Amino acid sequence: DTQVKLAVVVKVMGRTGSRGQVTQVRVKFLDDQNRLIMRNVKGPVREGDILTLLESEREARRLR
Amino acid sequence: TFKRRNGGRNKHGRGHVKYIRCSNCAKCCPKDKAIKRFLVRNIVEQAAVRDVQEACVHDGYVLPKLYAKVHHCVSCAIHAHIVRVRSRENRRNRE
Amino acid sequence: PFTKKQWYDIKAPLLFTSRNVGKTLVSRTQGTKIASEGLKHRVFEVSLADLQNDEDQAYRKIRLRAEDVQGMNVLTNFWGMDFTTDKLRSLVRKWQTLIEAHVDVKTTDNYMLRMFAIGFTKRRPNQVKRTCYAQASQIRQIRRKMVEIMVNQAASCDLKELVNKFIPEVIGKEIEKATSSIFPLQNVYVRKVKILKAPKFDLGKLMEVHG
Amino acid sequence: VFGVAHIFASFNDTFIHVTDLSGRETLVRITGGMKVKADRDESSPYAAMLASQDVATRCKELGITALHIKLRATGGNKTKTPGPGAQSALRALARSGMKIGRIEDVTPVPTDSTRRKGGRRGRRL
Amino acid sequence: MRAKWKKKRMRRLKRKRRKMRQRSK
RNA sequence: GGUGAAAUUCUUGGAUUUAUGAAAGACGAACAACUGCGAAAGCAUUUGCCAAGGAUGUUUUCAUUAAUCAAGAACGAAAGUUGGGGGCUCGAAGACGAUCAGAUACCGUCCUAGUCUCAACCAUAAACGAUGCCGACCAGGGAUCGGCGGAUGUUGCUUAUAGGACUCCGCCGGCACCUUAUGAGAAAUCAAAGUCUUUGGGUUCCGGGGGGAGUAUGGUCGCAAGGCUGAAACUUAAAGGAAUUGA
RNA sequence: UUGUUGGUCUUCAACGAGGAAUGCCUAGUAAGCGCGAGUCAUCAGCUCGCGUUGACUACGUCCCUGCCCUUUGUACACACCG
RNA sequence: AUCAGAGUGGCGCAGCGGAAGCGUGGUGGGCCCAUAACCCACAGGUCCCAGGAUCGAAACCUGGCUCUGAUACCA
Ligand SMILES: [Mg+2]
Ligand SMILES: [Mg+2]
Ligand SMILES: [Mg+2]
Ligand SMILES: [Mg+2]
Ligand SMILES: [Mg+2]
Ligand SMILES: [Mg+2]
Ligand SMILES: [Mg+2]
Ligand SMILES: [Mg+2]
Ligand SMILES: [Mg+2]
Ligand SMILES: [Mg+2]
Ligand SMILES: [Mg+2]
Ligand SMILES: [Mg+2]
Ligand SMILES: [Mg+2]
Ligand SMILES: [Mg+2]
Ligand SMILES: [Mg+2]
Ligand SMILES: [Mg+2]
Ligand SMILES: [Mg+2]
Ligand SMILES: [Mg+2]
Ligand SMILES: [Mg+2]
Ligand SMILES: [Mg+2]
Ligand SMILES: [Mg+2]
Ligand SMILES: [Mg+2]
Ligand SMILES: [Mg+2]
Ligand SMILES: [Zn+2]
């Protein structure tokens, strides 16, 4: 099974996608405040938003 | 017109240089002309180094690097952005 | 399908400080496919840093063959010596000369084995030159000395103390010091040892080397 | 307790193959194409990680805690670099909860090979 | 390589003409 | 497995994978270079043998024996031809799978001749530095390969030294490179493509608008494919080189 | 008069939110609502203005269509519809 | 002579009772500066003819019709 994990956008990196509709941010896990990983988010997002992750493992790559 | 003084390859005093196969398309390209890069890259990138560094049994374990010497024909190197079309003046720069 | 397999403990000979290399598993002894002498010839791959607990030699992959099985205890003798890929590909680099040698050699017990040795020229301090190459004649002088030494240092009593020359790099630094009035030669090693031919069983010798 | 994990991560697929310390017994062998349905995406890091988690479960039920890793590309007279699934397999076998004993590369590199497929002008598309 | 292929065409036509002349023997 | 995606293909007579070993044939990675050797084509695993070779060194020898070359001759990538050997890989032709309006293609699969080797042929390549060879003069510089000479100052070297490794300087000889006109050129560019209307060191080959055409014919060489030699009628006002501005 | 237009009664069609395609739009904006003027003896389903009610989404990108500048190739210059 | 086979959109073919299409051409739109390709629709039909059986037929049985292929041996 999977458990929904909760993360915080700590810095926002850029705008990926063909049409720039996706942002790339670095998130930080609230339970383990040592695991910082890259994710892609759809929709407006600033520094400090809390992102819900259905799975935690998937980690984006630079300029994905 | 003659684009370059070296003819596009590094051959002086020889008559024949053995060819090599392009790493992407297998095109035969002489060794002195192909675009040769030596890549020393890590086993995993830095987002996923520590969740292997914490799973090392031994203290002081150093994760290897992969070393590969990659050749490209002119077409594949140009298309893969390994080398770029430069201006007439900056073509002469070998640095 | 795994309720029919027993584990065995594999043991390396006493010339290696740390022992008990690991655990293998075979399938429960059935007549005709009895495990004990049915397999009897597994080869295992263990680093030398697990056999001497010093990390300055995490390269130098030891290959160990099974010569006997004593009741859930697989006895093991030395089969081969190699490098790890990362080690060898760190050593070869542009602007320097690589010297290769190999020789077929006999030890006093009828073991035929092939030694491959590798070296590279050393730049000195205060060198302003941008390369360090030998002249294919110095190359030949070094390779001649390299095979000479490699055969005179081998052909000693047993693989026991031959591997006791491999462990602390007697061959390598002896070769470096021997060819220094020819060319400096940093990073000299015995890159591979392939044993060409193993004579017989010789059961007593196996416990002479084991424990 | 140790088993050795041969990750053969080529393009078009990734194999996670865990075997004993002699390579002579298959503990569990799961490939990328088992965890997906479309051929295009067998090599995807997603299939690599699903196969990794599955072999993790099959291994911790066999008493092995720590795995020795032997990475491999296709090699031979072809590409020497691991595919897209090699990295994900290590990442997931490490984060899934298992120890990694030692890492090294087994891609077959000829000291020189036979001729490679395609012809003199190469695969041109 | 139209020059090369034109050369091939001329080669073919010359072979054909030779065959007519040798058949005339 | 393969691909952008697929299919042909293999597969519970177990494919792909893993491990140890054997056989076979081909290839000689990395080192490997604005580096070497060779008349060019070309030559990259070790060791041994055989003859050959350039450069350096020289207070050795001969004494003009030389340069370039009709005739004539040696060598000459790959493909190709004939016959043995071999036959891993890749693979003209071919058979299928796709793509497409069609696809006798590009892409994928299976493959024949071939690729390898021996004996005999063939004699052609963008066989290119698109630049024949010998000689003289002409500018600056730093590298680099071979040899030699001269320097104190250090080696994990060496019964001490000498020497080998490195540093600095110089001279011959190579492969090249960088900066510059006082030069040349239609310019691109070139330290030789300079020393040309202020035109003459020697010699061989070779061009005379574009096509027709490397064609026809005759000769000659070849087993053959073809090689060398090589027109005319007719036709046509441009074809072409370098650079500039635009698109 | 092939009904100018406005009234009265009667007649009660298609149309069940629309295939491929495609347009305009970033705040008092889109959309909804009506009013004025032009035309004008009469005729506004149009155009030009005006107020009224008043949002969704984004705060990007160069994927498609194009535009500007640079470098590059060119056998194009009526210029790639070459 | 007897028998097996085939008749379904203007053409070639598929259709397992619940019952109609595929491919190609036709007409009208779309895409493009335009033409082909390509996209979307709309119109097409005595399922060869007559019976019967059957919840239910172009299909199953029978009968008549038109085209194809066949066995036709000892004198
Ligand atoms: Mg030379
Ligand atoms: Mg050549
Ligand atoms: Mg198998
Ligand atoms: Mg050399
Ligand atoms: Mg080699
Ligand atoms: Mg074909
Ligand atoms: Mg010629
Ligand atoms: Mg020429
Ligand atoms: Mg020449
Ligand atoms: Mg020198
Ligand atoms: Mg010099
Ligand atoms: Mg003339
Ligand atoms: Mg002429
Ligand atoms: Mg031009
Ligand atoms: Mg009116
Ligand atoms: Mg009005
Ligand atoms: Mg109007
Ligand atoms: Mg071009
Ligand atoms: Mg050009
Ligand atoms: Mg023009
Ligand atoms: Mg056009
Ligand atoms: Mg139409
Ligand atoms: Mg059209
Ligand atoms: Zn390529």
Image (cartoon, coloured by chain):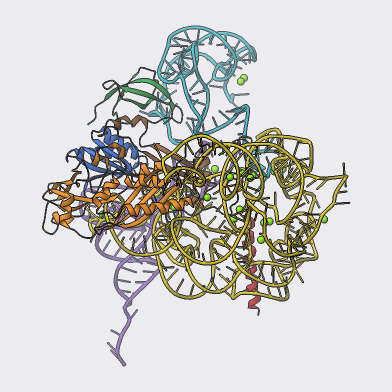
Chain colours: A green, B brown, C orange, D blue, E red, F yellow, G cyan, H purple
Give A63 or F149, whichever is nearer the viewer: F149
Which residue is painted at 34% across and 57% down in the image?
A: C104
The quarter in which the N terminus of chain D is drawn is top left
Residue H71 image position (x, y, % from top left): 31, 78
Which residue is painted at 46% across and 29% down in the image?
A: A19
Residue C64 image position (x, y, % from top left): 24, 49
Residue A8 image position (x, y, % from top left): 33, 20
Q: Is residue F122 above or below residue F136?
A: below
Give B82 or E21, whichever is nearer the viewer: B82
Q: Is residue G57 left or right of residue D4?
A: right
Q: Ligand 23: which quarter?
A: top right
Residue H62 image position (x, y, % from top left): 26, 64
Q: How many marks?
A: 0
Q: Is residue D51 above or below residue C101?
A: above
One can see residue B24 in this view = no
One can see residue D60 in this view = yes
Q: Is residue F82 left or right of residue C34?
A: right
Q: Is residue D55 above or below residue D118?
A: above
Q: Is residue B49 left or right of residue C39?
A: right
Give F142 or G35, whichever is nearer the viewer: F142
Give H34 or D101, whichever is nearer the viewer: D101
